[PDB]
Structure formats: structure tokens, C-alpha cells
Amino acid sequence: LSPAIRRLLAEHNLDASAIKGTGVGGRLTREDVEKHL
């Protein structure tokens, strides 16, 4: 992740609730929201 990942959701205004975080344990990574962008 990066220090800009947090502001990345507040920049494009997107609900992570609609995105699936298949991270290592059900976490939200960047390869998940990106596909949505």
C-alpha cells in the first residue's frame, strides 16, 4: 500500500463496501480498487 491509498478513496469518492478485498485475510489492497477505477 502507499500513503496515498487512503486519500485515493476520498479523491474519487468510492464505497469500498462494494469492492471485494481478497487481501491476505479479507483485507482491501490496491489491486482490488484499481480494477474498479
Image (tube, helix red, strand yellow):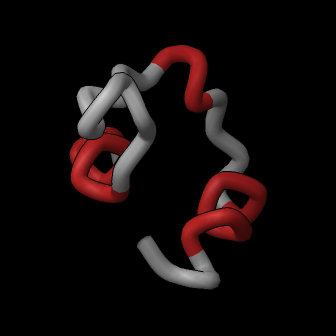
Q: Residue at x 36, y 24 (%)?
A: 26
Q: How many marks?
A: 0
Q: Position of residue 29 (x, y in %)?
A: 36, 50
Q: Is residue 18 above or below residue 13?
A: above
Q: Is residue 2 left or right of residue 21?
A: right
Q: Nearer the viewer, residue 16 or 12?
A: 16
Q: Quadrant of residue 5?
A: bottom right
Q: Is residue 20 above or below residue 5?
A: above
Question: Which residue is the extreme one toward the bottom?
Answer: 3
Q: Quadrant of the N terminus?
A: bottom left
Q: Position of residue 22 (x, y in %)?
A: 25, 28
Q: Residue at x 42, y 35 (%)?
A: 27
Q: Is residue 26 left or right of residue 2?
A: left
Q: Residue at x 67, y 64 (%)?
A: 6
Q: Quadrant of residue 3?
A: bottom right
Q: Position of residue 9 (x, y in %)?
A: 65, 54
Question: Which residue is the extreme one toward the front?
Answer: 25
Q: Nearer the viewer, residue 14 or 3?
A: 3
Q: Position of residue 37 (x, y in %)?
A: 36, 50
Q: Quadrant of residue 23?
A: top left
